[PDB]
Length: 266
Ligand SMILES: CC(=O)N[C@H]1[C@@H](O[C@H]2[C@H](O)[C@@H](O)[C@H](O[C@H]3[C@H](O)[C@@H](NS(=O)(=O)O)[C@@H](O[C@H]4[C@H](O)[C@@H](OS(=O)(=O)O)[C@H](O[C@H]5[C@H](O)[C@@H](NS(=O)(=O)O)[C@@H](O[C@H]6[C@H](O)[C@@H](OS(=O)(=O)O)[C@H](O[C@H]7[C@H](O)[C@@H](NS(=O)(=O)O)[C@@H](O[C@H]8[C@H](O)[C@@H](O)[C@H](Oc9ccc([N+](=O)[O-])cc9)O[C@@H]8C(=O)O)O[C@@H]7COS(=O)(=O)O)O[C@H]6C(=O)O)O[C@@H]5COS(=O)(=O)O)O[C@H]4C(=O)O)O[C@@H]3COS(=O)(=O)O)O[C@@H]2C(=O)O)O[C@H](COS(=O)(=O)O)[C@@H](O)[C@@H]1O
Ligand SMILES: Nc1ncnc2c1ncn2[C@@H]1O[C@H](COP(=O)(O)O)[C@@H](OP(=O)(O)O)[C@H]1O
Ligand code: NA
Image 1 (cartoon, rainbow, N blue to C red):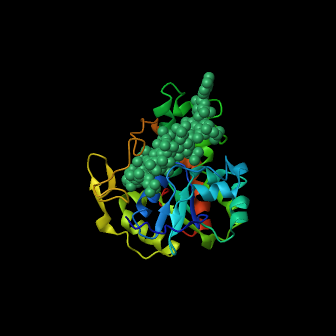
Image 2: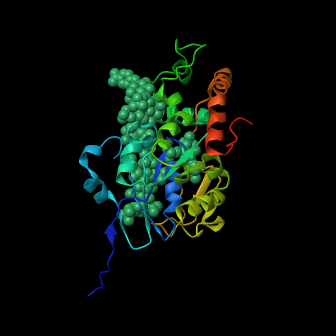
Image 3: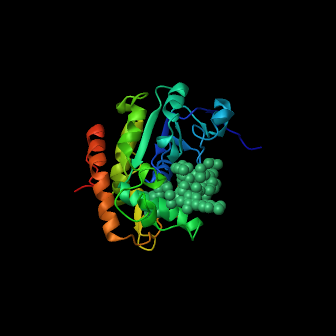
């Protein structure tokens, strides 16, 4: 009795949020889902890093259906640091657009540690993990929480397979302070009309972050959940200064590669 509509085909994603871990990848994808021309995968696929042997038909079948003109997207934050991922994504399509939501490497590292802490309460201290010798002097650049934050090093690998014009570096800090402004730039990059705007957001004082007045799936207000916007433990103040000192030259190189000063160093 009801009219059942064509929902279109499943397309491979024309744009992927490839990083960074704890940069604000869920927030960005959630906000983009408000747009009538966006369809997104929910959970992180981890195709190009973990499930690549399943093949592209399996990956395609994970995708939402789309009507003509809609963009298909997913986010997997580990892609950015996955050595094989640039070649593999280019093999799917050299024209894929890539979004990297970046964040102050120091708060990104603490966020990453705090995520582990929320699931494993008796992990070692952040300060012990920061140093080779677990006390001072030399920073353990091999520790994942520090290594992920050296964005210029990972970016080099991507630029061997993509032109930088196909990459957008989104400010995780501005995504919080001015979500509508940042989403304006994202919509431009994706070729989307600039529909997501200031009126889609409000500041939730209890959450401490922007929330959506309406989500794609909700007539009611939507904040991200308990795993988003965690209270960080306090980190030793001198350790923080040392980590900021370690990242500064790498940050400046990243500003030079991307053409933008993200403000993490004054
Ligand atoms: C409203 C509306 O509209 N609605 C609508 C819609 O809905 C939708 C929506 O929209 C959306 O939004 C949603 O989404 C969602 C999703 O889905 C979900 N998912 S799930 O899956 O979960 O489900 C979610 O998501 C989220 C979550 O939450 C999270 O979680 S947590 O918890 O974690 O937080 C996630 O996360 C993730 C991340 O991200 C990742 N990253 S990357 O980068 O990787 O990518 C990951 O991470 C992880 C990893 O994995 C790992 O690795 S491995 O390999 O290992 O595995 C890593 O690990 C590491 C760590 O971290 C470290 N640590 S530190 O500290 O350094 O950092 C290390 O660890 C270590 C330590 O250290 C030491 O200590 C230890 O030692 C030991 C141990 C043991 C022993 N014994 O045993 O004896 C001894 C000693 O060790 C350790 C180890 O090793 O382990 O290291 C490690 C490793 O490293 S390397 O590098 O070397 O490798 O990391 C990790 C972490 O975490 O960190 O993954 C993760 C996860 O994991 S698990 O496991 O947990 O699983 O994710 C997130 C995201 O975002 O994604 O949620 C969401 C949402 O949210 S909100 O907010 O937004 O709310 O969805 C939805 C749905 O879909 O439903 O729609 C719908 C539908 O519709 S349609 O139409 O479409 O159909 C509707 O209905 C509605 O209404
Ligand atoms: N509106 C929002 N609500 C909640 N978290 C937001 C947000 N906009 C940005 N974020 C950031 O998104 C981070 C998580 O990034 P990802 O989804 O890539 O793992 C959070 O880390 P914190 O928990 O350290 O605050 C938080 O700072
Ligand atoms: Na973590």
